[PDB]
Amino acid sequence: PLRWPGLVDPNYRVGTNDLPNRITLYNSLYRYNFTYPTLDGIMYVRSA
Amino acid sequence: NDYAAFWKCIASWAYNGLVTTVLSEDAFPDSSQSITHLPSMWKCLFLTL
Amino acid sequence: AQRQFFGLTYNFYGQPAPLFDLNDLQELAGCYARPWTSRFSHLAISTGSLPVWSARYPSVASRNIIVNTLLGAHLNPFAGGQVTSHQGITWRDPVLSSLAPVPAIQPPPVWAVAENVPLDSNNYPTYVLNLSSMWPINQDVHIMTMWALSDQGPIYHLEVPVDPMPAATTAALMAYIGVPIAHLAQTAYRFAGQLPQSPDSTMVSTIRWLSAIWFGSLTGRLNRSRTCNGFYFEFAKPALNPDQAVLKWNDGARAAPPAAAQSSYMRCISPHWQHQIVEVAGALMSQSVTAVTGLPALIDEATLPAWSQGVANLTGNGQGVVPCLDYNPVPMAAARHLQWRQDGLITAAQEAQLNNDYTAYALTIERHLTAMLVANPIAAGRMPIQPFNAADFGQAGQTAAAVALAQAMFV
Image (cartoon, rainbow over all chains, first blue to last red; front, side, top):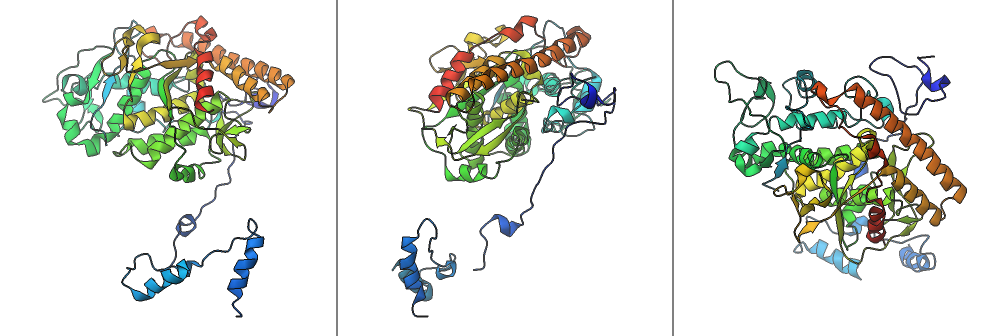
């Protein structure tokens, strides 16, 4: 169970790990939906 | 075109908050231009009226 | 820009020498690289992605604490006007670009150890003459000072003008909507860090508002019900991990500006700050503004450790003195929840539940830290975490005054 604290340990708190000493396999993470506007999409640019 | 813009402007009044009629961007004079440039000077007159 | 600053080195907690070993320096400021903007290079969105839970540097604040102690051994030029060496290491150049072992032919004089050393920029003329390149020093020295002045949490400054927000700040904030606090704090640190700026700059006003909004939401005065020009912060559920906040914009009623300009200094009175990212980021972000604009006024000595009593250019007890408030997160959370119920966001049943969850969460932080201290006794020669006593987790501090300030700050 040591490698699965976030799946079987009742006392597991979100946001913890044992990274420098052990590698867990089931944790909580974030995911993103970034968008990448071009320069013209950022500012008011048109022809003269 | 039977002066469609004029009637559209009048009609837009009854539906403001749903549609807003605006002056065309190209109607504006060039920003870098100077007042001495007569064609640009005329534009402001119409733009103001 | 700003051609002058003042500073104060750390205090030794009874120990005879600054608290860091060679490996600390070798890792945190080695590689002959510039150490002057590294503070965020070892931070991320949340604790779950960080090694802060074990081994060396076993706390969120640990690395930055060590950095502050490290600088205390090498900032002599702003104290005595000369570059020195400590344990065989010194700056490579009068510009203080980076550290290196001492040369064998003409070593600089060895630094005489001392603590709580006052610092002036004027003591080292070459700094101003090279302000364009040595500018990053200003920010870090300020940050180091703002932490050194206090036990428990670092000190930072708050203020709100009587005017509405300018349009530029509004547009900028409208681009930072879905961003967590940690990323925002980085940009504030990045901005003021790398080149001189005038206080009359758009970003400076922007960050000033952010610190205000952060505190107002922290106290719970700013909510979905009541917002600052449409903005406010949202905090994560205590049931999972309350140590997270993001920016929001909303249709809620907008708070009126205060009758008169409000301002004060702040700090966390309890050790919880050492392992709580929202506290660290909030402090750093706020401290960044003061770094570029300088201290508006002297800080009140009334509630500060002994070494902070009457420090020149920093602390005072005279007329032109701004009081400093402090708070404990647990009573703060209870107040925030209470405000939510009064605003009608939640029911009384939920409010009771939220208090139970947050108290349980805080207990873990205390339990972790107190166990971590005995694992790293300060007598070992390095201080990864600031010392404290068990009773320090129970102090209510001036929390009641703090929420009163936000009450007056966002009417």
